[PDB]
Image (cartoon, coloured by chain):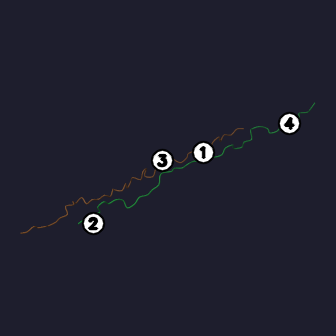
Chain colours: A brown, B green
Amino acid sequence: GAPGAPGSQGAPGLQGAPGAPGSQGAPGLQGAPGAPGSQGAPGLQGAPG
Amino acid sequence: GAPGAPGSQGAPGLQGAPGAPGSQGAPGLQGAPGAPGSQGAPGLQGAPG
């Protein structure tokens, strides 16, 4: 018998992993599908004179 | 050790642009302006005197 001096790596099976999932489906607004840039523009377009 | 442990697995990539739907524009107007009437004086001085 003698001091086993087995050493060890108590660091767990957790394995760190500082890397987020990555926001795979989270691109802000998945690309902001918000309103159209415009929907009209012909102004003062009447007729009679 | 961690023989293949994909520890901290994140996101191999990204990318996609925001919704910028149709921006309508400005049609003209004034089909056939011609303020409806008989241009000039239909009639030749109506038998003067």
Q: Is disc 4 on the same chain as disc 3?
A: no
Question: From the viewer's perspective, is residue B29 above or below residue A12?
Answer: above
Q: Which dot, 2 or 1, sits closer to the camera?
A: 2
Residue at which label 2 appears: B4
In the picture, the disc for residue B43 is 4
Badge nearest the viewer, 2 or 3: 2
Identity, as a three-letter code, of the amino acid under mark 2? Gly
Residue A18 appears left or right of B32 = left
| Residue B28 horizontal side relative to residue A14, left or right | right
**Lower sequence index among marks 2 and 4:** 2
- Confirm or deny contact between disc 2 and disc 3 (CB under 8 A): no
Quarter of the figure with the N terminus of chain A: bottom left
The residue that label 3 is drawn on is A34
Toward the right, the furthest residue is B49
The CA distance from mark 4 to mark 1 is: 44 Å
Say what secondary structure mark 3 lies in. loop
Pointer 1 residue: A41
Query: Callout 1: helix, strand or loop?
Result: loop
Q: Nearer the viewer, mark 2 or mark 4?
A: 2
Q: Quadrant of residue A2?
A: bottom left
Kind of residue sitting beneath label 1: Ala
**Mark 4 crowdedness (10 Å alpha carbons): few <14, some 14-19, many ≥20:** few
Q: Which chain carries label 4?
A: B
Asked if disc 3 and disc 1 are in contact, CB closer than 8 Å, the reply is no
**In the image: residue A8, left or right of residue B33:** left
Chain ID, mark 3: A
The residue depicted at 60 percent of the width and 45 percent of the height is A41
Say which element carries label 2: loop
Helix, strand or loop for disc 4 = loop
* Residue at 36%, 59% in the rendered image: B11
Say yes or no: labels 2 and 1 on the same chain: no
